[PDB]
Image (tube, rainbow, N blue to C red; front, side, top):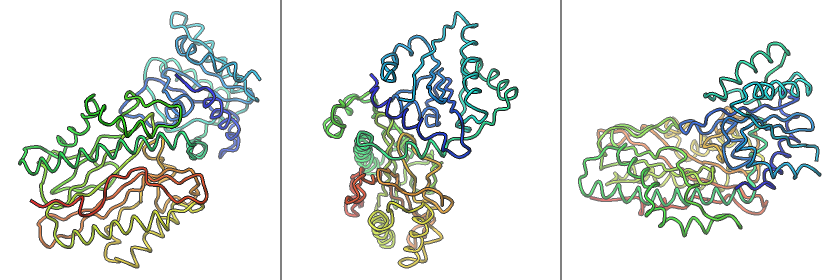
Length: 441
C-alpha cells in the first residue's frame, strides 16, 4: 500500500522544479520496461521508488504543464486510482491511461496521445538519458518515440542532475528508513566479523567470495531476520510498520584479504582462500524500503605495529572529516581538497595511497554519480538533510613484516540533520575501535 499524500507532495515538488532544470525542458518523460534486479538504480526506477515506494514495470509517466499522465496496465491503474481525487481540488490533473494487451490499436493510440501532449508543451523533452530497459513494452514504445523525435523536432535532453537535486534532501521518514537500513548493515557486519574469526580459528577451507556469500545468504534465513527485528523495527518512522519483505542488499557483501585489495566501487570478492593474517576489509550495505546504506570495516589479524598505527590515523581521519570538513554549503571538490590538505599536514607520505574520493551522497541510489565526493564535482553544495556514504582508505601500503602489501578502508552512512544546530549523525554504529576489530591467533 502506497502513501498517496507522499506521492502527491513528491510529484508536486518535481512538477514545480523541472522547467528550471538545465536546458529548460517543457516536459519530462519516464519510460520503465521490465525491472532488472541486477541494475536496480536507474533514474526512472528511482523516480518510481521515490513517488510510490514500488517500481511499476511497463509504465510510462509524463509531466507536461497542467498534467501528470501515467500509461500502465488495468491492474496497476487500480492501485493508483485513489490518487486521482487528490488532484481534484493544484496545478496538476492526474490521468491514468489503461492499456489492454488484447487491444494493441488502443495501446498505440495511448502512446500517440501522450506524444501529442508532449509536443503541445514544447520542443524540449527531459529524459534520464543513461536509462535503459528491455522487454515487450519497450519494443512497442521505442519505434513510436524515435519516429516522434525525428518528425516533431524534439530536443531531447538529460535531466539526471535536475532529478538528483530534487530528491537530494531526505525528509524525516526517509531519514528513518536510512537509519533502519544502516542498523541492518551493522548487524550483518557483526555477523560477518564473527564468521570471519571462526573461519580463521577453525582453519576453514573457504574463499573470500564464499564467506561473503554466506553472509549475503543470511538475508533469507527467517531465523536471522527474526533476530534482527527488534532493533530494526524500533528505528522505523512513526506509523510505518517494520516489514521483512522490504529488506534487501544494496550490493553483494565483499571480503578482501591476502594478495588483493581493491578500494574502488567496482571491487568484488576474489576466489582466493581466506587469508587469516594482516588486513581483512569487509563491506556490507543493506537496503530497507529502497533506502541504501553502507559500512566498511578493516579487521586486523596479528597486525604489525605499523598496520595498527596507520589504523589509528584512519580513525582520526574519519573524525576530522565528519566533525570539521563535511559541512553544509561546501562543494565535493572543497571537501575532498580539505581532506588531502589534512593528510598533507599529518601524514604526507600517505597522500599517494589515498582513495580518489571519500564516497558519495546515498539514498534510493547506492551512489549518486552527480554527487561523488571528489575533485571533479565543483557544482553541488552540501545541504542539511543530505545523507552520505563516507568511504575512504589507503591502498598499496608497505608491510615491512609481510610479502603482501596491505590496505586500510573505513565507511559509515552519515546523516546531515535538517536542524542547523545538530552535527552529522552516524547511522552505522558498529564498532571501529581498534581493540574490537583486532584479533590475535
